[PDB]
Image (spheres, coloured by chain):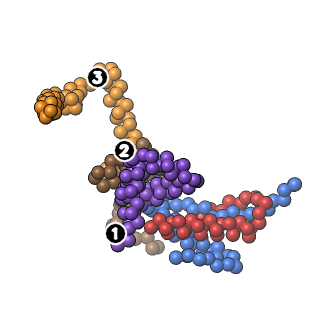
Chain colours: A purple, B blue, C red, D orange, E brown
Amino acid sequence: IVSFLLLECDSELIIASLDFLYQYILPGSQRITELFKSKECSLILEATLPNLLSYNIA
Amino acid sequence: SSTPLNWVQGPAIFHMLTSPYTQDEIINHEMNFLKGRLLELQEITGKKITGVN
Amino acid sequence: AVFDLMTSPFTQEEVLIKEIDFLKNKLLDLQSLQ
Amino acid sequence: NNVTLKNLTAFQLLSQRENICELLNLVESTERHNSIINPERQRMSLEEMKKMLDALKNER
Amino acid sequence: SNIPDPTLPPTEMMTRFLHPNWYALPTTVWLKYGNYNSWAPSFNENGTVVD
């Protein structure tokens, strides 16, 4: 799912992945730990989120 | 009858002469039909609609 | 268009209002598609 | 590049008929079966595999 | 009558006739996600006739 986040040419897929991750980490903090336990998910999130901030806004 | 019913002249269903099985011609003729039926029903009822183009 | 005589616990007015609502939503969706 | 009912039915019927005619041994498909296998291409690919394997072997 | 003379063009019937047996059914879509995006949904087969 975070790999789906890594795409660029599909806004709807990115929004779906972000909505799933939002609903995932929403109820509490143990799920945040389980999410960031994986090194790959952590790296992809760290490289993706700031660039998703400036996504298609010129 | 324990449930009183009425005679209701139902709604117009879209019917195209040639059904082409794809969405392009269907969507064109269907937008036309939708606008026409909205105009007809707005003429029938004492009401107004928003977003009619 | 085709009209089919039917029967329901509603009245003609409520049926026309429901048709207006549904057709408005459908036209909005078809417009948003393009 | 376009697909209609006629094209689909013709394609499916052609596949079925080819299979059945092959069951009765009423067809000779040596050209197709040797253009798909392509033993020349087999030898070429085998030699390429051997060269790549030697390359990976000698880099150590 | 308003009926024209039988020698005046046009004179053909099925010049723009299309039988439903050739109506271009729906099929797969074959999307393309960049060049290095291989973990990506390639098809879009929602209302297709054949897989």
Dot 1: element: loop
Q: Residue at x 33, y 20 (%)?
A: D24
Q: Is residue D54 left or right of residue E36?
A: left
Which kind of residue does numbered mark 2 sit on?
Answer: Asn
Percent position (x, y) of residue A39?
Answer: 39, 47
Percent position (x, y) of residue C11?
Answer: 77, 66
Q: Tell me the tag on residue D26.
A: 3
Report crowding for label 3: few under 14, some 14 to 19, many 20 or more residues within 10 A (C-alpha): few
User: Which chain is mark 3 on?
Assistant: D
Q: Is residue E25 left or right of residue A32?
A: left
The residue that mark 2 highlights is: D7
Dot 3: element: loop
Percent position (x, y) of residue C13?
Answer: 74, 70
Q: Report which quarter residue B13 is drawn in.
A: bottom right
The residue that mark 1 highlights is: E8
**Separation of residues labelled 3 and 1 (CA atoms):** 55 Å
Q: Can residue B3 be seen here?
A: yes
Which kind of residue does numbered mark 3 sit on?
Answer: Leu
